[PDB]
Length: 107
Length: 7
Image 1: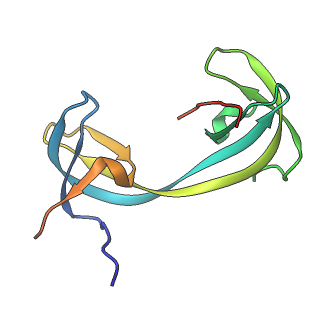
Image 2: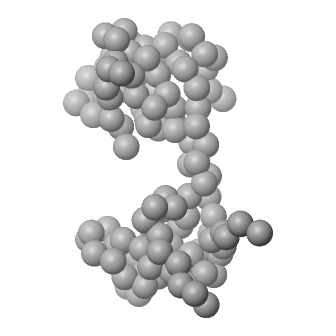
């Protein structure tokens, strides 16, 4: 079988403070990213649905709120669901991270 | 991640 991370798993991940700490996986959650081709010719495949001012159809014209607070016109390409992990640290703080920010233990 | 590019 392929290795997997599951709820309750003791692992090592990055705290919001940037440092690594042992933590526990509280639950698996799916994050959905949107991909769009901007009118200016560039494209982003890591926007969140909250950045559009179900998902639109490929080619559909949409307005995207960028990181600069400005709105740009674009056409929707596709949505990308990605398996992610909600982990909780010693102080009780919690975070949703990707596979690459998680280091598993042998037991 | 909100990153853009022309590829």
